[PDB]
Length: 214
Length: 213
Length: 11
Image (cartoon, rainbow over all chains, first blue to last red; front, side, top):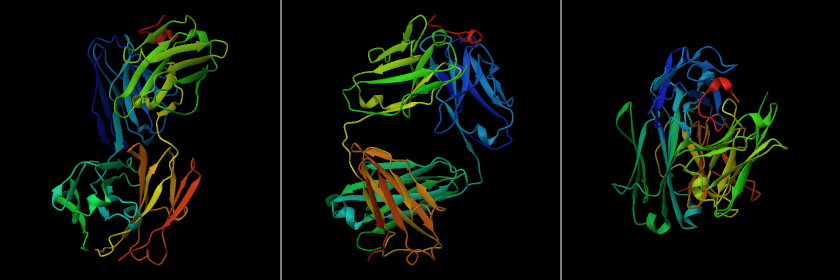
């Protein structure tokens, strides 16, 4: 197989700027390279074939690669429509292999999260399952360490983390962190904490609640 | 010259087989290779193999050769790909491509689950707790199957500060979660209600989000 | 069969 190496993995760009993604093949793929865009929720769209030929329809802001073993798709000036994951593919030989993609998101001034903590509902406890949910809303950038600490001690098992794709109204993102415990396992502990390390705030952002009453 | 049409979503049991279709339109079927590619969050894009509708030649990936069977039917200008002995690692998006143009995708979910309805659990803000210049309510729909599940907040009319997260899998079932950020001078008067509907079980629960000491 | 594209073919 031909390890295909695409860098960066993700990038933070603004409308108007010049984008460059690179594709590196483990062998000479004889300019047998294709570039294509995956818009979230959609089937790939071909942009460039055999290293440098623009697919019909494609705007001329898009332009392609080199030869030998490293190739690039350059976007002259970035436009909104261009936000999706980009992927390169070699078809010089079988099997056919793809690069790991490059995700493009819109960039902004930093914004820190609004964190909210919710002890289990009575109802769910009355079924004997316990859910400690935590919401970390409207931050940017996308990097955020969510750490759960029960009565002081950090626990990392039984924790689901769902992410929101970068909102298109405010260019911010935000997760939902959830600890799950049983009724017996929740009522053995007292203090429950929601811990966040986020850039822009040097020290962890913590919300919390006590099972006695905080 | 035009496009490719894939068959709709498949919800199959482990141990079972499926057959995806790729009808081709607007060109000469037997002149252009059709290939099958697989998409997943872990591995991303993966090529299963290719068929030549005209020569009947096929090229398989060594990863899927014991599990994939590529066929084509000239008469109906449809590519078939058959996936057998289904396992939980076959859950994914499968595309048929002619390299320049692509089908829209066929979602295949392999699952041993049964129709299960959600538990919508109202998420009350710590009641014996702190305040600020805004209040965030919440809602939890834990344990359903299959997807989807559309939830709304005050029937889609209270939706400027709404957040709904993609449905995660746990224990074989789905759990989704939603968050509304409303003005701190609004909640207890103007009530906020979480509306949750699970078609498949034909259930529409409405849970009152109410405070509690 | 996409003559212009070149590259691997099943033939």
